[PDB]
Amino acid sequence: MFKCFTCENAGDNYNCNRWAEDKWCPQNTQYCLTVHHFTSHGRSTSITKKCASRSECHFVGCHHSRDSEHTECRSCCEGMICNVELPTNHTNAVFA
């Protein structure tokens, strides 16, 4: 089992943590979805993540809003609570 960030409305990474606690992921899941809401014009940016699978996000990518000019890029990262910070640089080591 593993713990992932299953937050909904979180303006910042910290907030996402306050909502999404350290709970085990579902049985029908093997990935950590990570949706990034980037506004074409505006500092504010929505963020949402949760457990997913190969089917749930079989066709990842970005989706530009029809009404607003805000795009939503969702991906699938592996590893316990891998969806820590939005701006992913690289993978760290294990302390096991």
Image (cartoon, rainbow, N blue to C red):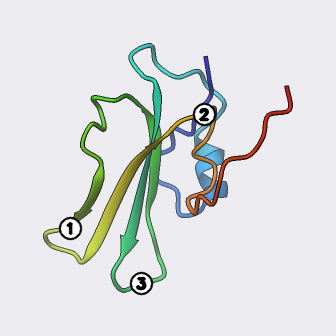
Amino acid under disc 2: Gly
Provide the secondary structure element on which disc 2 rests.
Answer: loop
- Judge left or right: residue 43 versus residue 60: right
Q: Which residue is situated farthest in the left direction here?
A: 66
Residue 79, label in figure? 2
**Vertical position of residue 29 compared to residue 7: above or below:** above
Q: Amino acid at mark 1?
A: Ser
Residue 14 on image: x %, y %? 67, 56
Which amino acid is tagged 3?
Answer: Gly
Instruction: State which quarter of the image contains the C terminus.
Output: top right
Mark 3–mark 2 distance (CA, rounded to whole Å) = 31 Å
Question: Can you tell which of label 3 and label 2 is closer to the viewer?
Answer: 2
Q: Nearer the viewer, residue 70 or 55?
A: 55
Tell me what residue is drawn at x 20 percent, y 67 percent.
65
Q: CA distance from mark 2 to mark 1?
A: 30 Å
Q: Position of residue 58 (x, y in %)?
A: 27, 36
Up-down: is 12 above or below 77? below
Residue 62 x %, y %: 28, 60
Q: Which residue is mark 1?
A: 65
* In contact (CB < 8 Å): disc 2 and disc 1: no
Dot 1: element: loop
Name the disc covering residue 49, or none.
none
Q: How many marks on residues?
A: 3
Identify residue for label 3: 42
- In the image, what residue occupies the spot 45% across and 50% down? 48
Q: Residues within 10 Å of mark 2 (few under 14, many from 20)?
A: few
